[PDB]
Image: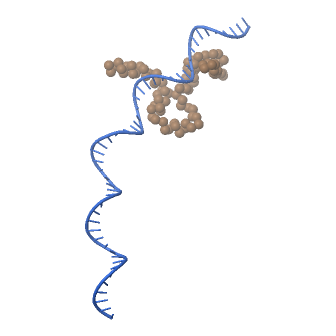
Amino acid sequence: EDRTFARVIVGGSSEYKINNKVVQLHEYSEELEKLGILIKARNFLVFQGAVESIAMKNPKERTALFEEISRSGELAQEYDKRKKEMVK
DNA sequence: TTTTTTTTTTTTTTTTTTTTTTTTTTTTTTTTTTTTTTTTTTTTTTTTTTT
């Protein structure tokens, strides 16, 4: 089988297509997440000059990336809400 | 030739200045936080247009 993804831009907004049918960003995203690519992570693209700036980042940004890939960023609000409650 | 007198060089002493070194104090750029504003993007209703 063969899949045809698309994305057309209108005005300011952008619309996504699956199998030549208009879809919303979230479901398209979820399909990609099934395929195995975390677009917000940005761990597999390297532009003109960033191959150096892969190494010299401040460690926090690298931790951010490693937290992003690992599906442990969604559990943030849960964490610090529990934190504030228990410290209170 | 020898004796007497003058002048230049060398070297030591001293005094003033300079340099050094640390220490303590001070005040400043640097670094982080928070906010927060802007701008871009988004949505949804309205408007326009088409069959």
Residue depicted at 55% across the width and 38% down the height: A51
x, y (%) of residue B27? 35, 39
Residue depicted at 47% across the width and 29% down the height: A64
- Front residue of A21/B45: it is B45
In the displayed structure, does residue A47 sit left or right of residue B50?
left
Residue depicted at 36% across the width and 21% down the height: A83
Q: Is residue A66 in view from this perspective?
A: no
Instruction: Say which quarter of the image contains residue A47.
Output: top right
Depicted B46 relative to depicted A55: above or below:
above
Tell me the blue chain.
Answer: B
Depicted B3 relative to depicted A64: above or below:
below
- Front residue of B50/A14: it is B50
x, y (%) of residue A39? 55, 26
Q: Is residue A71 in view from this perspective?
A: yes
x, y (%) of residue B26? 31, 40
- Front residue of A9/B19: it is B19
Quadrant in the picture for the N terminus of chain A: top right
In the displayed structure, does residue B50 sit left or right of residue A33?
right
How many numbered marks appear? 0
Quadrant in the picture for the C terminus of chain A: top left
Tell me the brown chain.
Answer: A
Instruction: Say which quarter of the image contains residue A37.
Output: top right
Q: Specify the color scheme.
A: by chain
x, y (%) of residue A57? 48, 36
Depicted A37 relative to depicted B50: above or below:
below
